[PDB]
Amino acid sequence: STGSATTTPIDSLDDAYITPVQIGTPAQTLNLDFDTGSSDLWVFSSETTASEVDGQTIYTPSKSTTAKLLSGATWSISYGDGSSSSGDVYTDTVSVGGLTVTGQAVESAKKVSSSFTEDSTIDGLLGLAFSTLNTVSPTQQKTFFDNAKASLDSPVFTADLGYHAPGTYNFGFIDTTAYTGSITYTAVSTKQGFWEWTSTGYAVGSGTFKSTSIDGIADTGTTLLYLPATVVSAYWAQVSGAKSSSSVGGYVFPCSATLPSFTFGVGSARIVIPGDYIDFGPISTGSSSCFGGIQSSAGIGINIFGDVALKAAFVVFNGATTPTLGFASK
Ligand SMILES: CN1CCCc2cc(CN)ccc21
Ligand code: NA
Image 1 (spheres, rainbow, N blue to C red):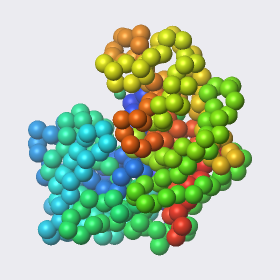
Image 2 (image 1 turned 90 degrees about the vertical axis):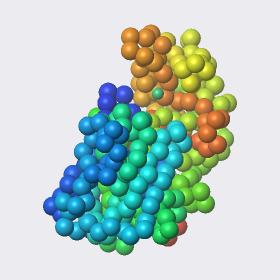
Image 3 (image 1 turned 30 degrees about the horizontal axis):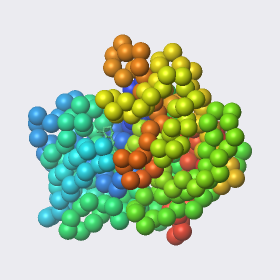
């Protein structure tokens, strides 16, 4: 089997991407944020505290003839930004882009943080990291990908995010029309439950490539590129008037600037992030200070190749017995 779904930016900055997901019988379509940095499929629901819902579409298990309460099971997650959600669990039929999983754990939110309530466009998250990070207790649950894997033509999914444009998530096949050149594969460590890999270095604009190992995770659920402070300082030093602002919470730059590209290594290959991808616009409405899309990881404890980096590539998440990542230009 295979599946193929379009993923759409939620706003003009590509802060996040939503993908339609069919849950239950008859289908209830919710727009979920596919998140390669977490392992819970959780949704706004008929159980969510009413004051914490503001425009999201909700899953109503009582309207699904295939929904079963997973008796005794609860979940609670805290994301790296400080956001959170928690609740109880149903199993139901879940379909993405024509690929169907029966008996998928659908984590129903009783509580969400204000940061989720405020995002009316996001109806929940579909985690695609390893199932060892799933938060359901007392019986840990599998991701949609882990449940689908055995049925897929090939045990893979691919992320093809757009810059200010829709893109695609494919499950079970590699669309050889969607990238240029060849795919360069690189080793993955699953020891922390992430798609963790090592980049071979970086360049700033037209500058020389610096060979240096940078461990990090491929995380579609994170907007920006978080890298070590040495690398980030080298990038922003090439932008007149850029500075790190403790008041704003990262590097800012004059909105009049033209940003240089950023290149990262994948083995002997190179992925080039155009400068425009690194512009996240005014810090507040009307400001002439703009927020940068490359930020320090120093306060995080991990480097994160989030959407700023991933949208510059066609990315293969290879879930074979020995997982690997693949990157291609596009
Ligand atoms: C609060 N916020 C809404 C936008 C999508 C989203 C995704 C994650 C997962 N990294 C965490 C928070 C969050
Ligand atoms: Na921000």
